Image (tube, rainbow, N blue to C red):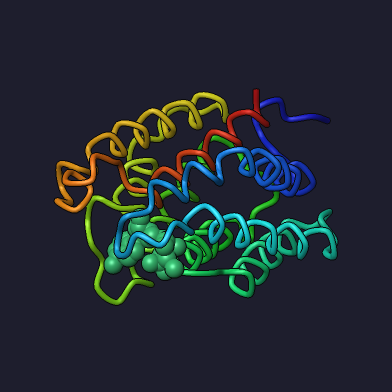
Length: 200
Ligand SMILES: Nc1ncnc2c1ncn2[C@@H]1O[C@H](COP(=O)(O)OP(=O)(O)O)[C@@H](O)[C@H]1O
Ligand SMILES: [Mg+2]
Ligand SMILES: [Mg+2]
């Protein structure tokens, strides 16, 4: 039977495929926001290449098993990771995959755990983390994910992420001086937005 408020392994794979297709519209905007640590206009391109490599790996895997979906997500994202945002994103996805290992379906409760473990894995991966960044936005999303149904969890996680994103120039002066929010954190918002679109 269908679980209504839970994704099977095939649906989890489709969610990330959907989110990848969603992401491409926002690439040019993310590039133009990129001021930290250097303004070289590539955050959107870097994050998209990371996502696209995860999708290529999922297409080669047996997405009927949750442990194979998790393996493809971590392994693909690492190889395709580009730049600081891509490396961090790949390690966020590795923590997300870790929460999926040993589980048969992704429900609201596991999605909270996955978002929280993703943020911690991304934080541990950076040698010297800085706040006002993708790390701050990813952590807020996991902390603010509430509810039992997927849709409520994604909605509350997204709202907490958008709220943290607006506060990034308050924490990082280079963002305030340039009048932008963090490009990496904005990319993570767009990724959560795509996931909500799949679940809606
Ligand atoms: N030390 C750090 N701590 C937290 N986040 C970081 C750090 N360094 C970079 N980032 C994230 O990476 C984003 C920049 O991504 P990107 O442009 O791909 O990096 P690069 O400088 O390699 O081009 C920033 O907006 C920030 O969110
Ligand atoms: Mg850059
Ligand atoms: Mg660069």
